[PDB]
Image: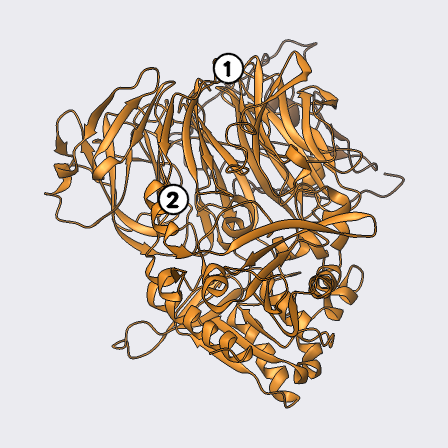
Chain colours: A brown, B orange
């Protein structure tokens, strides 16, 4: 349900957004025992919140991923998330 | 000229207060336990008809610790084999009895050693916690669905609380929250992985050869805290084909940047939830409002539905931030908030508007929001006669905030000044509980026209008994320091001759937002001391006390063991000035924070007090827990408030004790205020050559509440008092 052009959950919000200006496809498949050369990771991960807190220490501003790009939070989210609710923080320099 | 209220009277419970506890099960029906049968009463008229005969479980073959009937009256849950854990918590065995089938359910039972069980709020669904994992039963007699696989003793807690959340945040063992119709089950997960263990001995029965070392994750001020994560599971789409999916709802960004807590969980509608989070520096909290998303299956929490709450002069809320009561559509909500004058009043919020509008004002405070209909909000406050120590039920018209009417002040003015209320399912009827100054009175009312259909219980039998004993009187009044009123109460012996000079015993607690001066009627050992030993027993609410606004309450911010100690001394002086107090005979005593204040007073050098008893005292704030302590003190690092931490300890006053008689009492198994604190007190006292009395209680907790231990501690304290006052 969460991987669709019409979807508006954390996947298109913070993970992977494809072009709306080109013809587009989305295939879900399973690797059956036949081929053996692809290997499983520990668990499926995805980002469920990616936000900025501005310097006023009050305002939260979600960071949406753009088509054909990576979430700005890639810099701080591990390749595989350790446990189901983990959270990450990186303080920003005044320029940043 | 009758007999007095004696210590034996107090301990053996010879004069007992009757209660009347009911349980509403609908808009006009409640359950009572008359003569050990459960009956259902119909408020609309008068009738009453047996719901469950006492004989039903003559055949159980188990001592039955507790029961709970499901919302639809179809099933009853039977709790036996209760084995205690902390305070609010335990382990037990459970059996479910089908009321239709009149049979015990024997297939697929709830496992032994279960930590907690709740019915859903409307069906007969079951959520229980066992080995720290959540399990849901939809139909009571089919396999439970396991919700979490992650629970682990003393490390991961799913759906139940760890020590500190239990004691200082939720005041419960449960950390489950059903949605109104039981569709969703929201739960918390606590992680104590990096939280330090407190360890202590448990000696148990005389036959246990090697004592048991009890280990509890417990964060002390500044130490590493537990972490929290929040989940919601849809219980209607559970299945045995598939592990349940718990959607995690993540805390706001302003919380994620540092240590935080989850401090409130309130459902708004069948599909709207509100979460309140609090920063570890309890200056700052945020409410998040999350809607369920029928398509994606997740939970959407729009920013700008968030609501920030800050305190510029202390902490948020009285103890935690206050909970919201939503309207029926869940687009607006009412919430107790402290206003510009620093008095706590009801605020009316829109879920998408930052600003809120106050619906009550005044130099008095709203105690709690009790019920909310479309037309009226029912709330309890201490407005009447400007007494912070009284309580009454008010209702305010939602279309005209000027139309506020008082449902209890005129009911019985000289007898009833302390009310609490229990409302029927749609605020159709309500029961009023009166706690003092006269004997407790329990009545029933309909809220349609506020008519008082019935007197549930009046304590006539008790009144009868008390006629034939010399009871003490109670005075409740105030004094004026720096153009401000500070209330006190006194328990005065029978035949109180204003001319003679009585010994005085200060009863102290004095902790932040406390209140020992109230209108409640009590039968306790202060009654014994007054009735039998002709000794005046007094309490006083000085700086940093409750229900009088933040000018008084926040007065002790960042600086415990200062103003409230000073003020308890000042009150003994002020009591002297009244001229019926023999100032060569003032004791002071207190348990917990009151033990801390007692100790601090005895070590003050004031020379006002002859002796004191300190039961389970805090001695040094770096010993107590993080949540409570840091609320009032911040961190004990030197970047923060370390100076006030170290300046404020009992042990550093050891020398001064040479001027006073001191009795120090502590249970060996107190998981709350550790024996450690007193061990440190007695150590400092030994180290400066001060003599004192002491008493340990083997295996008792913070309550010293077990029968034998309780009569023992009061007997011992009685002897110490009678001796210190050189009375027969």
Instruction: Determine which quarter of the picture holds residue B107.
Output: top left
Give x and y (percent) for residue B330.
57, 18
Q: Residue at x 59, y 68 (%)?
A: B502
Q: Are marks 1 and 2 on the same chain?
A: yes
Give x and y (percent) for residue A86.
58, 43
Instruction: Determine which quarter of the picture holds residue B365.
Output: top right
Label ID, residue B133: 2
Residue B513 in view in this figure: no
Q: Residue at x 56, y 74 (%)?
A: B678
Label ID, residue B295: 1
Closest to the observer, B689 or B288: B689
**Kind of element beneath mark 2:** strand
Letter of the chain that mark 1 sits on in the rendering? B
Considering only vertical position in the picture, is B528 above or below B69? below
- Sequence-wise, which precedes: disc 1 or disc 2? 2
Q: Answer with left or right where residue B349 lies relative to residue B142.
A: right
Give x and y (percent) for residue A80.
56, 42
**Kind of element beneath mark 1:** loop
Residue B343 in view in this figure: yes
Closest to the observer, B214 or B490: B490
Considering only vertical position in the picture, is B400 above or below B445? above
Closest to the observer, B53 or B110: B53
Residue at the limit of the structure toward the right, as seen here: A95
């Amino acid at each position: 349900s969460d991987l669709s052009v019409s979807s508006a959950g954390p996947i298109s919000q913070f993970n992977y957004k494809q072009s709306f200006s080109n013809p587009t496809c989305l295939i879900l498949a399973t690797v059956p025992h036949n081929l053996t050369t692809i290997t499983k990771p520990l668990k499926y991960s995805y980002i469920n919140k990616c936000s900025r807190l501005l310097s006023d220490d009050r305002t939260e501003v979600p960071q949406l991923v753009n088509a054909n790009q990576y979430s700005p939070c890639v810099s701080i989210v591990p390749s595989t998330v350790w446990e189901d609710g983990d959270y990450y923080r990186k303080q920003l320099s005044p320029l940043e | 000229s009758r007999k007095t209220y004696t210590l034996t009277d107090y301990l053996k419970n010879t004069y007992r207060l009757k209660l009347y506890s009911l349980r509403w099960i609908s808009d006009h029906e409640y359950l009572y336990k008359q003569e050990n049968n459960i009956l259902v009463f119909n408020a609309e008229y008068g009738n009453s008809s047996v719901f469950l005969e006492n004989s039903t479980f003559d055949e159980f073959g188990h001592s039955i610790n507790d029961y709970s009937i499901s919302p639809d009256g179809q099933f009853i849950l039977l709790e036996y084999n209760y084995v205690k854990q902390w305070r609010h918590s335990y382990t037990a065995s459970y059996d479910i009895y089908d009321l239709n089938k009149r049979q015990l359910i024997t297939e697929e039972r709830i496992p032994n050693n279960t930590q907690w069980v709740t019915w859903s709020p409307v069906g007969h669904k079951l959520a229980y916690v066992w080995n720290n994992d959540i399990y849901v039963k939809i139909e009571p007699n089919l396999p439970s669905y396991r919700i979490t696989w992650t629970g682990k003793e003393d490390i991961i807690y799913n759906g139940i609380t760890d020590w500190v959340y239990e004691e200082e945040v939720f005041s419960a063992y449960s950390a489950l929250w059903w949605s109104p119709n039981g569709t969703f089950l929201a739960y918390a997960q606590f992680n104590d992985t990096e939280v330090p263990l407190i360890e202590y001995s448990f000696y148990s029965d005389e036959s246990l050869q090697y004592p048991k070392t009890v280990r509890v994750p417990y964060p002390k001020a500044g130490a590493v805290n537990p972490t929290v994560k929040f989940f919601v599971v849809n219980t209607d789409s559970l299945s045995s084909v598939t592990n349940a999916t718990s959607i995690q709802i993540t805390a706001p960004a302003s919380m994620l940047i540092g240590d935080h807590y989850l401090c409130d969980v309130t459902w708004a509608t069948q599909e709207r939830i509100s979460l309140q989070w609090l920063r570890r520096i309890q200056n700052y909290s945020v409410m998040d409002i999350c809607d369920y998303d029928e398509s994606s299956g997740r939970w959407n929490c729009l920013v700008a539905r968030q609501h920030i709450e800050m305190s510029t002069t202390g902490w948020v809320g009285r103890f935690r931030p206050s909970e919201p009561h939503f309207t029926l559509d869940g687009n607006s909500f009412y919430k107790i908030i402290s206003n510009e004058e620093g008095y706590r009043h009801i605020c009316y919020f829109q879920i998408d508007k930052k600003d809120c509008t106050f619906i009550t004002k005044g130099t008095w405070e709203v105690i709690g929001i009790e019920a909310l209909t479309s037309d009226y909000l029912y709330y309890i406050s201490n407005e009447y006669k400007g007494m912070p120590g009284g309580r009454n039920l008010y209702k305010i018209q939602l279309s005209d905030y000027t139309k506020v009417t008082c449902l209890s002040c005129e009911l019985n003015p000289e007898r009833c000044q302390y009310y609490s209320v229990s409302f029927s399912k749609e605020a159709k009827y309500y029961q009023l509980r009166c706690s003092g100054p006269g004997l407790p009175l329990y009545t029933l009312h309909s809220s349609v026209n506020d008519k008082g259909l019935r007197v549930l219980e009046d304590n006539s039998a008790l009144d009868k008994m008390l006629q034939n004993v010399q009871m003490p009187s109670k005075k409740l009044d105030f004094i004026i320091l720096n153009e401000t009123k500070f209330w006190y109460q006194m328990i005065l012996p029978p035949h109180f001759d204003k001319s003679k000079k009585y010994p005085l015993l200060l009863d102290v607690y004095a902790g932040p937002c406390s209140q020992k001066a109230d209108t409640v009627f009590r039968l306790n050992w202060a009654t014994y001391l007054a009735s039998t030993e002709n000794i005046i027993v007094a309490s006083f609410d000085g700086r940093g006390s409750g229900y009088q606004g933040d000018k008084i309450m926040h007065a002790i911010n960042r600086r415990l063991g200062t103003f409230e100690v000073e003020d308890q001394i000042e009150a003994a002086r002020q009591f002297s000035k009244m001229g019926f107090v023999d100032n060569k005979r003032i004791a002071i005593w207190g348990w917990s924070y009151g033990g801390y204040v007692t100790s601090m007073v005895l070590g003050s050098g004031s020379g006002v007090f002859k002796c004191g008893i300190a039961v389970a005292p805090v001695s040094r704030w770096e010993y107590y827990d993080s949540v409570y302590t840091e609320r009032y003190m911040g961190l004990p690092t030197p970047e923060d408030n370390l100076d006030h931490y170290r300046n404020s300890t009992v042990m550093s006053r050891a020398e001064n004790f040479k001027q006073v008689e001191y009795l120090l009492i502590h249970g060996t198994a107190d998981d709350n205020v550790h024996f450690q604190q007193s061990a440190q007190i007695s150590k400092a006292l030994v180290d400066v050559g001060v003599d004192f009395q002491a008493m340990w209680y083997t295996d008792e907790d913070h309550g010293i509440a077990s029968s034998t231990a309780h009569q023992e501690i009061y007997t011992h304290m009685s002897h110490f008092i009678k001796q210190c006052f050189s009375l027969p």
